[PDB]
Image 1 (cartoon, chains in turn red, yellow):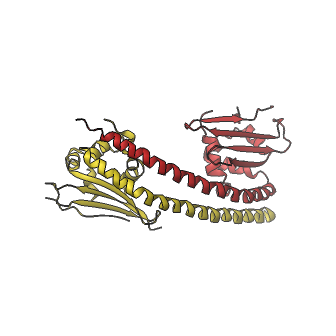
Image 2 (cartoon, one colour):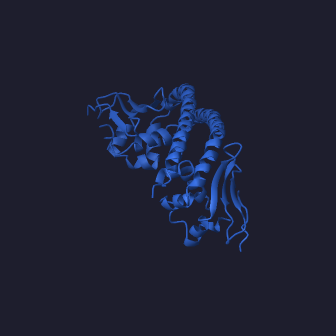
Image 3 (tube, rainbow over the protein chains, first blue to last red):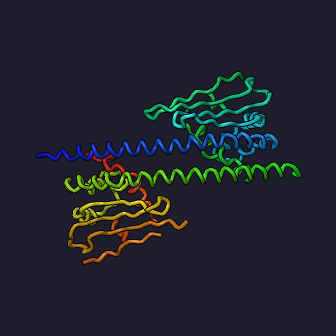
Length: 164
Length: 162
C-alpha cells in the first residue's frame, strides 16, 4: 500500500552510522597517539617562549579576534603571564583545558588560571574555570570560541601571528 | 635583537617539526578514510537499491534540502524527474578528488544516460558533455559539489520527510 521502504532506508542509514562511528574511533586513536607525541615538543617550545619577553601578549594583540578583546589594562596584566599551556583529554573526545600561568603579578592574586571544557555525549559542553582572586572576564559563556580559537588557531603556530 | 633572533629561529625549527609530525598524522587519517570508503562501498551501492523503489527520491531530497532547494529551476526539476540513480565516488586515494555521476533514464531532453562531473586535486573539473535534443549548466563554483558530497550524500534523510 504505502511504501515503508523509507524505514528500510532508515535502517541502511543507521547501519552506515556504525561504520562512521568506527572510523571516528580510529581517527580519535590517531589523534590520541599524536597528542602524546606532541606533548614533548610543545613543552620544549614553551622553554624557547620563556626567553622571548611578552611573546604571548604580542601574539594575542596581533591576532585580530582576540586582539579586539585586548582590554588594554587586561593587556598590561596579560604581559605578566609566564606561559600558556593547552592540554587535551587522554581520550581526545572528552574535553580540554587552557591554562595561563602568571609569574607573581599584581591585579591577580592567583598564580595560574585555567578554563576546562567537558563534552557531553549529546553535544552540549560544560565550561568551568578557576575562580579569580582579584575585559579578561572569560573565567567565570558565549561559546567555545575563545577557548576554541586559541586551541585551533593560535596554539599550534603562534609564530604566524607573532611576526605581523 | 641580536639574541631575540636565534630564539625566534629555534622556535621556527620547532614549529617546522610540528608541521612534519602533523603531516605524518594527517597521512594516517587519510588512510583510515581510504580504509573505510571501501567498507562503505557496498552499503551505498545497496542503498541505491532502496532508492530505486522510492519514486522521485533524489528530486525530493534536492528540493527539501535548504541549500539545494533553490538551485533547481523548473526545467531542472522536470529533468530530475527522469533520473534513475545518483552516485558519488571518492578517488582510489582520498586527497586526489571525487566524481558525481547522475544515472538518468531515457529522456526526451538529452540522450546521454549517465553524466559524470569529476573534480581532481592537483596539489581540475571535467564533465561529460551533454548531447541536447540553471543547475544543469554544470555540464569556479565547486561548492555545488561539496555540499552534495559532504551533507546530502552521506545522509539525504537529514532534511527529508516532506
